[PDB]
Image (cartoon, coloured by chain):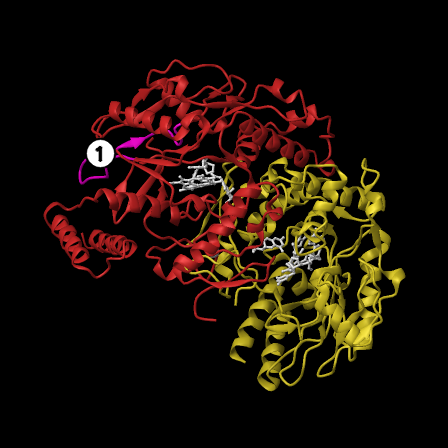
Chain colours: A yellow, B red
Amino acid sequence: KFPRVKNWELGSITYDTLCAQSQQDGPCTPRRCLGSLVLPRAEQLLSQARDFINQYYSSIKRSGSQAHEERLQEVEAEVASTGTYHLRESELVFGAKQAWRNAPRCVGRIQWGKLQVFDARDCSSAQEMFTYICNHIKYATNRGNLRSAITVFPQRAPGRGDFRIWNSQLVRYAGYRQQDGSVRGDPANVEITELCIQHGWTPGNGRFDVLPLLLQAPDEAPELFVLPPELVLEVPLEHPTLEWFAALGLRWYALPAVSNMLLEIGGLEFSAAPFSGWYMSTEIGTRDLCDPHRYNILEDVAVCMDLDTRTTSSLWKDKAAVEINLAVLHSFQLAKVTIVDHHAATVSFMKHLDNEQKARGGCPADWAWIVPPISGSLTPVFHQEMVNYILSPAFRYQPDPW
Amino acid sequence: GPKFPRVKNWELGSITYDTLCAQSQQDGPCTPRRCLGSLVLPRAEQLLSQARDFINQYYSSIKRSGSQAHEERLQEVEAEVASTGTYHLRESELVFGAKQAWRNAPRCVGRIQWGKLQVFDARDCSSAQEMFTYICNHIKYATNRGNLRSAITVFPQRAPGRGDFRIWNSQLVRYAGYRQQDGSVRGDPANVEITELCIQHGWTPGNGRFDVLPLLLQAPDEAPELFVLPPELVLEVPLEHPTLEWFAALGLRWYALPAVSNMLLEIGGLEFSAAPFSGWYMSTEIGTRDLCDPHRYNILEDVAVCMDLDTRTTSSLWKDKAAVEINLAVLHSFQLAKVTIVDHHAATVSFMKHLDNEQKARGGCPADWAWIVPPISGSLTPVFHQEMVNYILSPAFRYQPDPW
Ligand code: HEM
Ligand code: HEM
Ligand SMILES: Cc1cc(N)nc(C[C@@H]2CNC[C@@H]2OCCNCCc2cccc(F)c2)c1
Ligand SMILES: Cc1cc(N)nc(C[C@@H]2CNC[C@@H]2OCCNCCc2cccc(F)c2)c1
Ligand SMILES: C[C@H](O)[C@H](O)[C@H]1CNc2nc(N)[nH]c(=O)c2N1
Ligand SMILES: C[C@H](O)[C@H](O)[C@H]1CNc2nc(N)[nH]c(=O)c2N1
Ligand SMILES: [Zn+2]
């Protein structure tokens, strides 16, 4: 009923009691575990709303108070009359932080209480979305001293189409399918790149061309907006000891800003609610730059290092990957842009686990995502058993809107 | 697609559906409420149904399903259970079952080799002395002077009201761990308990970092007996680095033969409590887990100091750099000593081939992602990008709690 959770490095044991609060089923059954899958495939609104309002008044230590009773009344009155309701700004702020706190795949949750929430629910056009997005980027970037933020656009409504940001992140690089079937730039972005061109964008021809935004107001075709280049902070990549590295012309953007996820609070759904923090370096150094289906630079770098590329057992991939990760860290540090390495991040996540154990009796965590893509067992999270489950408020993946 | 789990590879975009999971007769620890896939230890009518299922599997495998020989074997199994409470496997049934248990092991990345397993039948064993003889024969055969051969030796099954055959050691070859006066451990901290148990049963201990442990072998209803492995039987590899000349001076070594000895082999409801098996190492297990785990030999800082890395800060990636060179030293040293070993890149490549093989042969492959993905360089290997479905099939290897 309550899972025992063991840490194999230290021998310590906890019991996860928080999982009993989960009201949403995941993909696993007693017959088979599907934990490694990336996307597994009024009365109800009212109970989700009540539970959320209960969570909110409990957080400000006012459970059972007058304000608590009357707010529940307002919610019931609104839902009974209209089939929906609306959150107060303070409730939205609480809800956004809780969705972050609840996110099982996020190693950065020690920071969960520190989040700037921009209320963009008064947005009525793709143009207004753009202005809000520009302000988010400026605030969050803060000349390299990154600040966590989320901008929340109008909720879904039974009648109409969603507000949507078509881009999966606010800042990404284009991928241009070449004549010879190869890709120039980021192969993950060929489709969105093609959509932008088809919506009137004049493309670059570089490996690191910042994509325009396609923003969608309800039941309208998406509209194209180019980010002012001064707003988009980038970091040229150099290596502390390998001089030829800077000459690879590699770079990455400062701000990791996820724009494709749905934010669910109290049964209400925010289909556009882009959020940003700061990078953990292995994501750039390992996944973005070294994934075979991404920039795939591993062999290039290894040849520059004069490593024997002919055989796996020289561990040329492992050596090149480490140096690339080092270059990312050195470069962001040099440019004075907030970044965290995987050792520091996982140490802080272990602290987060302990804090949550005391605060809530557990912490939903997805081990496959929490353990970094290099040097897994070198981090403390590798030796930590984790219990995974869905708590609400929650961030939810939504498929590309085309 | 159908009502079976959809399984995606994110590097290649390819999709399969796992239909094999329908064959699972045993619950794992997950529910719709919560996933427990990352936990190491998951929390006569019965016998006969497991037996029938296994016999059905055996006759399917030899293409005689529904035949007279198949029906007669089922009747023979039932009549034996009816009169004795148990039954016994034929030689070829044991061979099939042991191979199938390996094939079915979700945590094993080496399964491309599953059909090549030398099965030693030791079901005639009747004393701890004879267990020792069988184990020495296994080690000699498996080691083969460095040209390693996969093998399993199967001792008699669990029986009603009679004690088990048990090997107390978790592996046939492990190093001692000696608790020091200052609280530190000399040798392998993982083995402190077994080391102290060996001393209690009359072993004169060494005082090195790499002292091979004796075996504690238990025959039915007896105290375990102590047996020292003759040193000429235990092949070891001194560790050196191809370019860093000081590495050899560290005096590190590892043994050639990974031989797991504490797992239970379950076949058709029969339980083989002693059935040690062995293959060859994947290099990251030694280089990363055995040598670099904080709770094991913990040599990362030592090696990083020798490499002159800045160990005072995480962002120098000193742990990552040292771990890579230690892993390279292991591969290099085993290759130099002509002892079979496989790197994590070659092993995960072969496992992807295995997945494709099993997709065609059985419609899926149970696999534990957290164990298949190696402990360094995870996403540099193809298995990181492959979704995996985990479920329990029988025949199976199951973990056994220490007999103490
Ligand atoms: C402040 C610094 C932060 C760090 C270092 C961090 C770190 C990470 C990392 C490494 C991942 C896995 C990324 C991947 O491989 O795709 C992740 C995922 C995630 N993070 Fe955090 N994060 C931070 C801030 C935030 C914020 C501000 C939010 C929302 C308010 C958030 C919510 C999420 C969610 C929902 C995921 C899963 C995303 C997905 O499914 O693609 N994180 N984070
Ligand atoms: C032939 C070369 C082999 C290779 C390269 C290999 C590789 C591996 C690796 C890397 C692991 C994870 C070990 C750990 O981290 O503790 C593992 C586990 C396992 N292997 Fe294989 N293996 C091989 C042969 C075998 C054989 C012959 C058997 C049995 C017949 C077997 C059955 C298992 C089982 C049952 C586990 C899980 C053990 C546990 O739960 O502690 N493997 N293997
Ligand atoms: C198919 C699919 C499902 C899903 N849940 N998610 C995705 C995004 C993928 C996950 N892996 C790569 C890519 O995500 C890339 C974006 N990752 C940034 C995470 C981050 C880091 C620091 C601060 C933040 F605010 C956010 C795709
Ligand atoms: C508690 C517990 C549960 C469990 N299932 N397992 C264990 C042994 C642990 C697993 N992780 C480290 C240690 O096992 C160390 C032994 N692993 C050798 C694997 C191997 C490699 C090549 C060929 C083979 F035939 C076998 C402990
Ligand atoms: C198939 C597998 O689940 C998939 O490759 C996951 C593994 N772990 C991950 N972990 C993080 N942090 N981000 C990812 O995109 C992934 N991908
Ligand atoms: C907590 C976690 O499940 C545990 O540390 C696992 C992770 N993956 C592993 N994978 C392998 N191959 N061997 C192990 O011992 C472990 N340990
Ligand atoms: Zn699961």
Label 1 is found on which chain of the structure? B
**What is the magenta segment's predominant secondary structure?**
loop
Identify the residue at image location x=84%, y=43%.
A334
Which residue is label 1 attached to?
B163
Is B380 on the left or on the right of B388, as rendered? right
Is A18 on the left or on the right of A78, as rendered? left
Is B135 on the left or on the right of A126, as rendered? left
Question: For ligand 5, which image quadrant applies?
Answer: bottom right
Identify the residue at image location x=59%, y=83%.
A83
- A295 w.r.t. B402: above or below: below
Front-lying residue, A70 or B248: B248
Q: Amino acid at mark 1?
A: Gly
- Residue B241 magenta-highlighted: no
Whether residue B30 is visible, yes or no, is no
Stretch in magenta: B154-172
- B371 w.r.t. A90: above or below: above
- Name the outermost residue toward the right: A230
Is B356 on the left or on the right of B378, as rendered? left
Q: Position of residue B270 (x, y in %)?
A: 24, 45
Front-lying residue, B126 or B149: B149
